[PDB]
Image (tube, coloured by chain):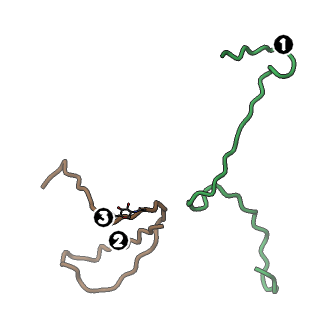
Chain colours: A brown, B green
Amino acid sequence: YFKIYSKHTPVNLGRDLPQGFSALEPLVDLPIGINITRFQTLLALHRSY
Amino acid sequence: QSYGFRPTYGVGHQPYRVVVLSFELLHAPATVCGPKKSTNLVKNKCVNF
Ligand SMILES: *[C@@H]1O[C@H](CO)[C@@H](O)[C@H](O)[C@H]1NC(C)=O
């Protein structure tokens, strides 16, 4: 299973990785089962800038 | 081959419907499960909870 922990944080002002503390909560799980070995993210390239 | 249904015919050739139910223990979370209904709740009484 893989759990997507996420904490939406709007306190940030725009600085690169500021200091603080937070915590993240589980959302959902789903089994697949594979030698993943790689990862990538595609981009919505139809609007490029 | 066409079945050739006969409404006036007796047993055998009359329409009989058979349905199947396939159960498998795949590596998946609890998906089709029927539990028991929860009984009432008691307070200030030493019971098994
Ligand atoms: C394990 O990972 C390797 C990485 O390339 C892959 O070639 C292989 O098929 C994987 N084995 C299984 C059983 O998934």
Residue under label 3, please give it.
A38
Given residues A42 and A38, the one toward you in this image is A38
Q: Are marks 3 and 1 in contact (CB under 8 Å)?
A: no
Task: Give the spatial CA distance, label 3 vs label 2.
Answer: 26 Å
Task: Give the spatial CA distance, label 2 vs label 1.
Answer: 70 Å
Which type of secondary structure does the marked residue at label 1 adopt?
loop
Which quadrant of the rendered structure holds the C terminus of chain B? bottom right
Q: How many marks?
A: 3
Which quadrant of the rendered structure holds the N terminus of chain B? top right
Name which residue lies at 41% across and 68% down: A4
Q: Chain of mark 1?
A: B
- The location of residue B41, given as percent across then percent down, is 77, 74
Q: Chain of mark 2?
A: A
Amino acid type assigned to the residue bearing label 1 in the image:
Thr
Give neighbour class at mark 3: few <14, some 14-19, many 20+ (Cα, 10 Å): few
Amino acid type assigned to the residue bearing label 2 in the image:
His
Residue under label 2, please give it.
A8
In which quarter of the view is residue B4 placed? top right
**Is ligand 1 closer than 8 angstroms to the Cβ of mark 1?**
no
Give neighbour class at mark 2: few <14, some 14-19, many 20+ (Cα, 10 Å): few
Name which residue lies at 78% across and 27% down: B16
In which quarter of the view is residue B45 placed? bottom right
- The location of residue B26, given as percent across then percent down, is 58, 57
